[PDB]
Amino acid sequence: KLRRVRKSPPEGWDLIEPTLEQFEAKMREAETEPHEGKRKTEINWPIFRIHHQRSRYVYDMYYKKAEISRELYEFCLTAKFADAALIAKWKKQGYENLCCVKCVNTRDSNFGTACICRVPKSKLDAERVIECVHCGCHGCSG
RNA sequence: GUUCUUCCGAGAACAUAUACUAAAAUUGGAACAAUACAGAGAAGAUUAGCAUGGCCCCUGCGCAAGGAUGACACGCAAAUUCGUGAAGCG
Ligand SMILES: [Mg+2]
Ligand SMILES: [Mg+2]
Ligand SMILES: [Mg+2]
Ligand SMILES: [Mg+2]
Ligand SMILES: [Zn+2]
Ligand SMILES: [Zn+2]
Ligand SMILES: [Zn+2]
């Protein structure tokens, strides 16, 4: 990754490097863990889950905590440490807990609806438990 | 879950219906390798090649071409119907 961004990490990369380096360890384990004893839908879920976490950590450091400068935050977007297109959603009102961009692509669904996990729980038959097939998200709206 | 309201623990807006839903459990359907036998179209033999037909395939990208002429075919073929005189009887 860092080879492919040419400039050096700008300012306080040491604050985020040990955490990002742990997400890398997580992601490689998720790639190589056996697909046996798991649903054909389940095995992809940790990938989307870890990719959500890592993007969320970079995002929270810059926006909520302000512990990294914009140049270091934008560096993480440039170095593909965080998905700019997922962070682009968490800025939108009503999307601030979105699990993955695949769940808001309405075009890919049979009827042109969003994913069911995007329905607010108060609008469900709220005893109902959800695990959406795209990522196992139980509900990510309200 | 977030941006706001305040009399204050509630209210407005944003957000709005994934998935042949199984890690399964059941249930049909093709060709395989070879002991011994007798062995591959045309009025004697060696026998071309190309056609023809249907509820028969295979190889091939194929309206090309190969697969024994790819194999088969291989006869009670009656399918619109009679007409005659002798000789027994009774
Ligand atoms: Mg011949
Ligand atoms: Mg031929
Ligand atoms: Mg031949
Ligand atoms: Mg023939
Ligand atoms: Zn999702
Ligand atoms: Zn979903
Ligand atoms: Zn979701």
Image (cartoon, coloured by chain):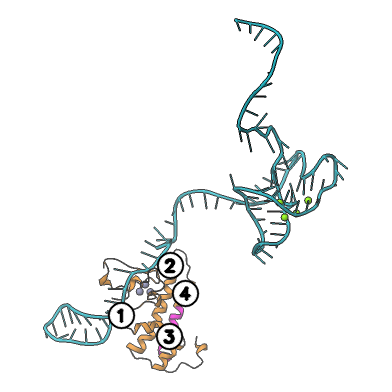
Chain identity of mark 4: A
- Circle 1 sits in a helix, a strand or a loop, which is it? loop
The quarter of the picture where residue B35 lies is: top right
- Magenta stretch: dominant SS? helix
Query: Which numbered circle lies on residue A60?
Result: none
Chain identity of mark 1: A
Name the residue tied to disc 4. Answer: A29
Judge left or right: residue B32 versus residue B18: right
Mark 4 residue type: Glu
Circle nearer the N terminus (2, 4): 4
- Looking at the rendering, the stretch of residues picked out in magenta corresponds to A13-25
Query: Which of the chains is cyan?
Result: B
> What residue is at 46 percent from the left and 88 percent from the top?
A78
- Circle 3 sits in a helix, a strand or a loop, which is it? helix
Circle nearer the N terminus (1, 3): 3
Mark 1 beta carbon near ligand 7 (under 8 Å):
no
Q: Which residue occupies the foreground of this view, B23 or A135?
A: A135
Query: Which numbered circle lies on residue A94?
Result: 1
Name the residue tied to disc 2. Answer: A41
Name the residue tied to disc 3. Answer: A18
